[PDB]
Image (tube, rainbow, N blue to C red):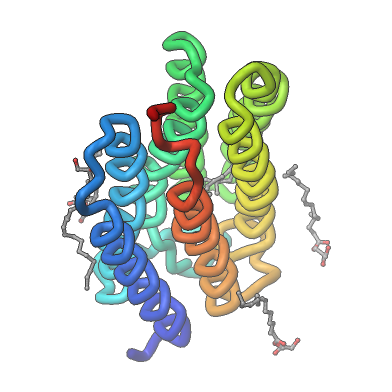
Length: 230
Ligand SMILES: CCCCCCCC/C=C/CCCCCCCC(=O)OC[C@H](O)CO
Ligand SMILES: CCCCCCCC/C=C\CCCCCCCC(=O)OC[C@H](O)CO
Ligand SMILES: CCCCCCCC/C=C\CCCCCCCC(=O)OC[C@H](O)CO
Ligand SMILES: CCCCCCCC/C=C\CCCCCCCC(=O)OC[C@H](O)CO
Ligand SMILES: *C\C=C(C)/C=C/C=C(C)/C=C/C1=C(C)CCCC1(C)C
């Protein structure tokens, strides 16, 4: 392929595909209703990402957006992926702590605003307005991070020890990895253009695989996903 970033899109496609297959074989035979919920949510995440990394590799999920004079290559398929996978990841954390319906709706709604305004900012043609949408999307993300710390952590500390310890590890992983996304976007091709697209694609690939495959490896190997039975 003539695009220098193709090597990272192909590695991303392969790793998401291998991750999906591993979780699929692993979830076979699980009869506990609670564990089936976590396996279903956690296997769909890499399956969706696989299809959208493939679409970028083949060129379907790419568009040209004029801003700053030149034509800029914008991979819109990322936002179709994140629209469906980031809510599912939040659902994994909320069900682990047995969150209430009201708090779950708050997280999913703010997540939808995060991704939706990020997409609008990505396709905006007036350069200075791109950063207005970036700001609003980052405000929605800070609300999500606030709820995970000053809401879920308080309840996790009144549950089973395995639930509290597993949640604390996954909460920490989420806060660090998610926080990197607005930074890469800001200095990358969608924003200031300080980092070239080939390096930007490499960074997102490392973050995406860690946040979906690595996240799932820690969750599905813990005993917190199974109900307390004899
Ligand atoms: C799990 C085990 C795997 C661990 C893997 C962790 C690696 C993460 C990669 C990071 C960024 C790489 C940045 C490389 C930047 C190269 C850009 C460059 O030097 O270009 C020069 C330019 O032409 C003139 O300034
Ligand atoms: C090279 C391989 C490429 C990557 C693979 C192609 C992915 C796209 C195809 C299919 C969906 C397959 C099923 C995905 C849904 C899994 C949900 C699940 O397994 O849930 C378990 C639960 O316990 C049950 O009751
Ligand atoms: C818990 C529920 C799980 C639900 C899981 C649902 C997964 C469907 C996701 C993705 C493939 C992306 C489809 C993107 C559609 C693009 C359509 C299109 O045509 O692009 C616009 C324009 O027309 C182009 O030229
Ligand atoms: C908790 C998560 C926080 C997420 C939100 C954190 C936002 C702060 C980021 C960036 C401003 C960086 C500088 C912007 C000005 C760009 C002009 C410029 O000087 O280029 C960059 C320079 O070469 C090299 O720093
Ligand atoms: C599939 C993996 C994860 C962790 C995806 C995370 C995506 C975000 C946290 C997106 C953040 C954005 C914000 C807050 C502002 C700029 C636009 C983005 C959509 C990249």
